[PDB]
Amino acid sequence: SSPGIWQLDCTHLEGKVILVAVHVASGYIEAEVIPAETGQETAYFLLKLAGRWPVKTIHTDNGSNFTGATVRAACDWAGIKQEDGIPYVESMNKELKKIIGQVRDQAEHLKTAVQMAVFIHNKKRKGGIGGYSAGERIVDIIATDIQ
Amino acid sequence: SSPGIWQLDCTHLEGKVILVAVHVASGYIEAEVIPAETGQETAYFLLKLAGRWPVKTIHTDNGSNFTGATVRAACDWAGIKQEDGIVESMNKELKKIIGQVRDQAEHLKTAVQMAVFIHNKKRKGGIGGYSAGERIVDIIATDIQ
Ligand SMILES: [Cl-]
Ligand SMILES: [Cl-]
Image 1 (tube, rainbow over the protein chains, first blue to last red):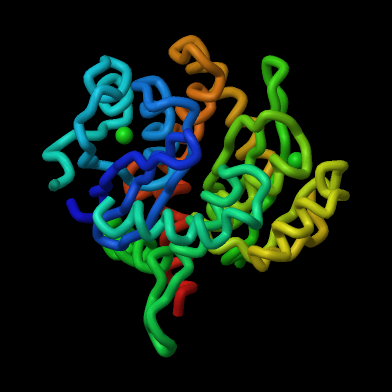
Image 2 (tube, each protein chain N blue to C red):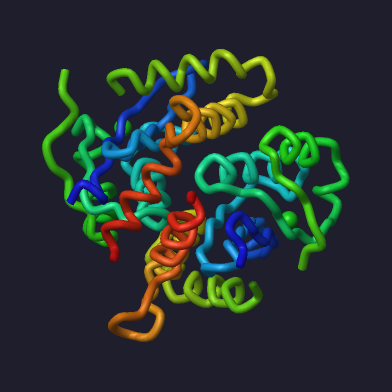
């Protein structure tokens, strides 16, 4: 259920393609620059995500890199179901882009900045006492679901 | 035991370099093929790991890709401390699983992720048993408080 639901969208910066996976219930993110927006590279990214978190369902934009039997085969193999797409990334790709822009000049290559931004986003809280970061929220949700 | 303790080791296959990070207490793995065993690529891999899990300390082989200011600056920036350093049972397995699925993948990188998936989803001892994936989350969940 909610524990295994992720949204996958693409973002573009400096002629590069970035795939962003958001764990809906927590706001937690996994993002990476990929060589091209193809089924082969999208399948690779999804297989990487699935081996790190319990991915059960994904909501994508259902674009071209999903019509090929590549991504379909990967989702099949990993036990991932593809459902309804994203509406029309909302305040995520922009937010992630915001952090990236803020730290872009601190890294030589874009890939490093992307990861610095993912780190900042997932460790971000919302006040003292509790607050809870997206990183803590995802772990709590999955923990209190597998037990 | 080890809330944010990870071991980072390198492995080589088909003329390529793979970085393997093992969460000591759970056995959970994060591994990827990197373009070269350099400080710049090692720092990249560590930053990626650090943004996905609460990494506090890493045990590495303290080799050449750790003498450069690159990895030191990355650990510093992420708040990671480098300690003693080199499990072996989790690593060796990775190569075996990779060998069992290499044929299904066009590129090695894909086979590696397939292997990571299989390893982290592996059930402890059938029924009631726990996978490394479930163990790492349960460990960090109880640590948050
Ligand atoms: Cl996409
Ligand atoms: Cl290494």
